[PDB]
Length: 54
Length: 54
Image 1: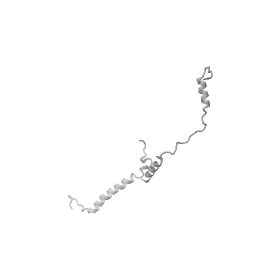
Image 2: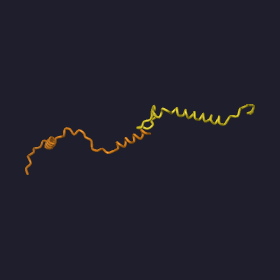
Image 3: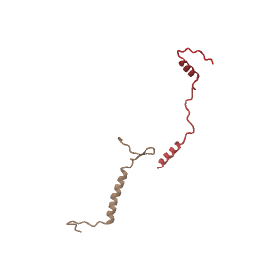
Image 4: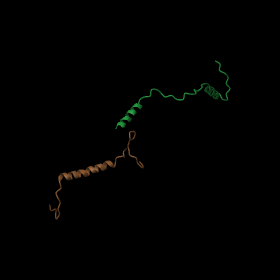
C-alpha cells in the first residue's frame, strides 16, 4: 500500500505544467534569399521580364 | 451406551468443538499456503497473475 501511495505522489509530480516549451534543433537557421530567388525565378520561368518602373 | 448392538463412549464437547475448529483452521492454513507467492504484485500494474495466455 505504501508503494501504491508512492506511485500516486510520483504521478502528481509529473502532472504539473512545463515551465517552458522544449528546445530543439534550431541549428542551421534557414536563408530567406534563396527561397525568394527560386520562387521568383520559377514564377518567371520562360518569361521575358522587363523591369518594373512606376 | 448400546448404540444398536454397538458401544460408543460419549464425546466431550470441548474436544470435538476444538476438533472441528482444528479442521477448519487447518483448511484455513492450507487456504493461505496454496495462494501465497502468487499475487505477482507491481505498484505500476496492480496484482498481476502471470498466465500462459489471456
